[PDB]
Length: 424
Ligand SMILES: O=P([O-])([O-])OCC(O)CO
Ligand SMILES: [Mn+2]
Image 1: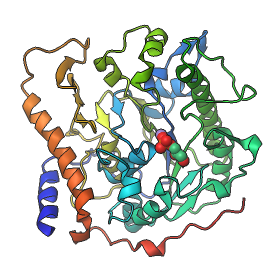
Image 2 (image 1 turned 90 degrees about the vertical axis):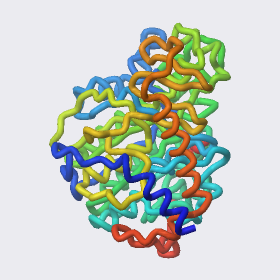
Image 3 (image 1 turned 135 degrees about the vertical axis):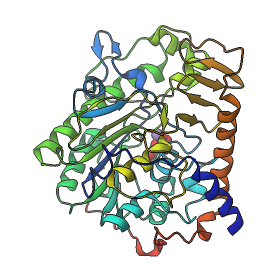
Image 4 (image 1 turned 90 degrees about the horizontal axis):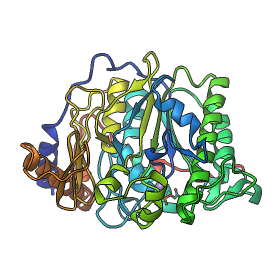
């Protein structure tokens, strides 16, 4: 078992990258605000429906002219755990499981998570806020193992009928109430806001909608237009509130889609909406779910690096100025010159700058045309993808952090974490 951990640690060493001196430590002990966009795909960016921009605020952020650096080639790497898989990868730089939910199944594994590292190295307190109850996706148990200090679940918000739709709290009230809670917290904090309204089947009361549905005939695609606009408006007002509360200028703020919202079941309607046949290659392209990051003292822009959610943890750690040599991570720092531009997907497909590998076939990213003669680096990349998934799975299945005496990590005692019922 210890030997199994050793094999994984040795494997994760080669990819390690040095921080970019332009970015190294620039956000040390600054508040970090992390905003989850439920089911958000970047095909929405700059998309109009009936002449209206679906997501006008995110469109502005994606210009690069609004203090955020936008990554247009950024992919979720999730499976059956959906939001829970995204959360798992974002805070650990590990993959979820190939079947089922790592949160549900591995919630009492030992972890060396991002929030715990920030707490230990720099005195952060970490929190999650979400307008649903705490034991969904086993979050209550998992967060204690991740070393999250506070969980503002649905008991912290008014869950009356007027404030809820679909799975729980409406995003607009969620963001408003959440900014109010953040204003009352001691710095430095690491705060993760998990949204909810832009979730299958994508239903929104007419009174709350500010855009008409598309007319594809597919209720899922047509409804998605409205819930995406609603989320964009919710986020815009949230950013305004941060400015009013003095929580904008000196915070790291990152924004990310958790995973795709529209499956291949909806290919007929998506062809109508996007004006292009949804081939397997095109569907892979549509798994772009976006990353936006604002860093104090840095201007925004557009960074075309191909990347995945596994890369977020080492990025944040390097921004804080924390040495990552001893952390078992599969991702690499987005701003580092040596960033590894290979993005494994959970099903064994993958993407690189130049090509994608989808259901056993290779396509050029330029035109999604089939590539007939193997790229020089293909076998190397395919081996990396397969081994990354196997090695990550070995950590989870073997609960291998039990055996890691990490000099840069103090073992979490999960029993020291408790999330009290909120006032509402
Ligand atoms: O995992 P999902 O289905 O994307 O999101 C659902 C929730 O976060 C529920 O609280
Ligand atoms: Mn989700």
